Image 1 (cartoon, rainbow, N blue to C red):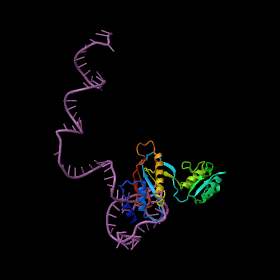
Image 2: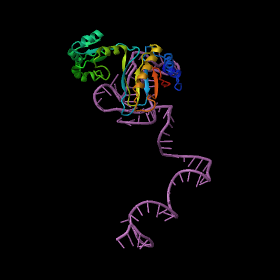
Image 3: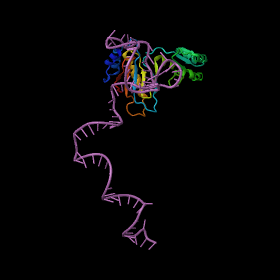
Image 4: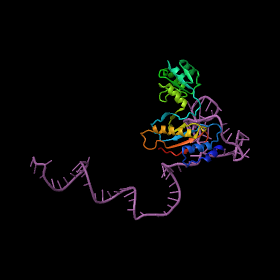
Length: 221
RNA sequence: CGUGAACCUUUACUAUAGCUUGGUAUUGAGAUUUGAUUAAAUAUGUGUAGGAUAGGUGGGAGACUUUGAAGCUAUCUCGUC
């Protein structure tokens, strides 16, 4: 009923901008609970091309994430000073192997990767193993913690050239949602492979928790 | 003997008349059908264990609810029945 009404109130042939689409979604928002609005981008993706990056959203609208630190020497103390939700050691590795999963993400130092290697069979189930590609493993443990606090998220491209990121929540302001979407679009464009000629992104739409997806006018300036 | 002729031969080289096949112009109206592609409608997707038909992605814990709920029955498309 509510979904039918929202679908009726959404126009598929209309090309509304980001703010207009956010306003329409908020008006058609029949989900009583605060809903995180996602963005689906169906762009030109190459067969052998991999699309993956990480971007810190301009506003932190996601719930707190348990940031764990795995480092030796002064690395654990530095993470604790930066505000690590959990600071661990080989004892932390043993706790994880026992089932220590009260945190949302795990970051490790280059040395702590020696113990984190045993975390492949444990962390690899959820994909939380430390890595340098996503900034989880690096010399800036404080930088990774700050990005996680700001709401850094990893974007990936599907096998059909599609991606589905989170731009915030319905309760978040229209300006905040627009800023997050613009930052994500700019990051995607900058990651757009130069080996492809034309439009890197074909279409972009925004869908709420239950609201029908609305495709915005894809204009790059 | 001459980087000379002529005619003749052929699975020597390169062309060509003739013959042949397709497109197009002369050259129109119809109908049926096999397609392909364009989108849109719409369904469909069962390793294993597992509550069971778990295709994938992410948002994702509330949503739907006389605009006919649970869910009874008949029946249809798929069925790995």
